[PDB]
Length: 230
Image (cartoon, rainbow, N blue to C red; front, side, top):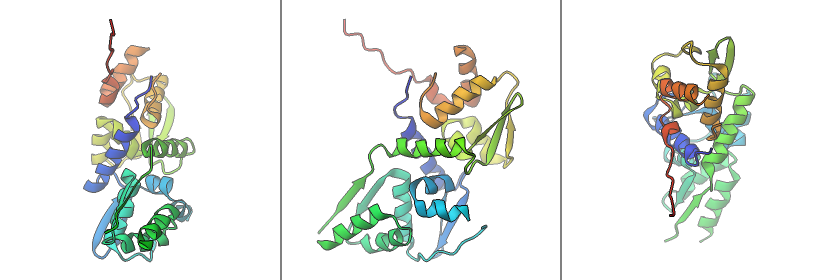
């Protein structure tokens, strides 16, 4: 069975982690403002960032508008952009540096013209989650392994924390890169859980629930609604 809001909930959590500083792994400082973010989301949104990361502790970028950076980030984390003649140049200079062709063409359009322009990339959640899964299957940006009876599972701290309060609480307090789970947890069970965290699809039903409870993955308990029409 599928959990059709799962992706969205993950993106909203990843976004909230950002706005509070929690569980991020990189930071932009510009004009005194700090913006924390996750490499894996940046790279899933932008070929520029992906390429930048194949190369360094620190890198200098030729962006100087903070509000602009702030909105490109917001877009990457919510799939919404609202362009006005108040902000269009800001955004444009940032999108131009990052070679984000979408945002650029949209800025050019608005500018060719009171003029407002909203964009929304449909099913963004889904797309981003798919990229995070793919990254995960190759060890890209994974900053933790979860060991279950000798089997290591690579993953992203931030994604696990998006679905599990156990992992949210653990990673907010410790920075250890290896994590063992209680002996009751089986590899097949954690597997299914891991797949659900990364895909929104779930397929012993008791041990799975036990494991979900220990991880405090509340969304798995949402069974939906049966509507009997007679």
